[PDB]
Length: 222
Ligand code: HEM
Ligand SMILES: [Cl-]
Ligand SMILES: [Cl-]
Image (cartoon, rainbow, N blue to C red; front, side, top):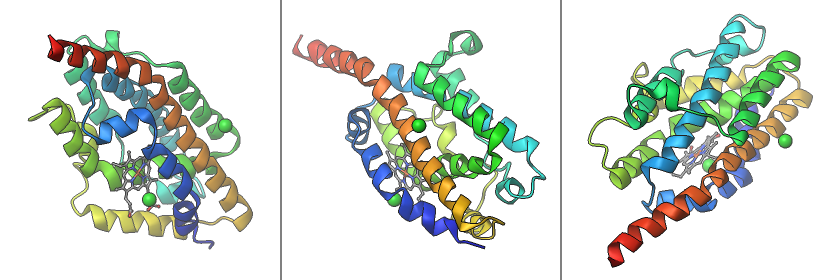
């Protein structure tokens, strides 16, 4: 009805660019990532996806959300697998959520009570990004931390054979959404909001990464 697929893509161009330039991210890209700080990121996303996937299931048959309801995208379980790897068997007891992460979860829950359609901005921001960057991020992680196997279940969509073909069904799904350009714009704005929320989680880890860096180099000089 409106073609938000291209509106979201062009509309979040700037934000995605700022995302790549966050200190934490810059270091990640250049291969310097470390188990302890990255472990906290996984804990946060774990709660955000839980929130999002639970609410999305309530709207499996909603006039709008039902169109972008692909339980094949669900990351909660794979993320639990990663916590197990980074934290071990007692992970339920060691995993925690940060303030930014809580704010993130809070927004998802809020939007789900008064503007369920804004949930497409959240599904878009996470899932379509996970789908598109998943392979690059996985290798960089695997190389920078040595994860021959385990620790990257999050970047692997098991229940999706042809992912490029899924990425189309998904964009298509968005382009066939029963919404008016007015709201389609509230969705785009919400997407830029979500990006900022991801970026805030990354910034929370800057300090943890600095120490770790100082520690490895100090150990090197010694
Ligand atoms: C704040 C964290 C990030 C979020 C929320 C995010 C989300 C997204 C979204 C929603 C898209 C789909 C755009 C579209 O086709 O409409 C996308 C594309 C992509 N992202 Fe990210 N992204 C983030 C950071 C990164 C990072 C750190 C990299 C660099 C390794 C990256 C690599 C990519 C790639 C390679 C694509 C595919 C571009 C294309 O379709 O031509 N992303 N991302
Ligand atoms: Cl992009
Ligand atoms: Cl905000």
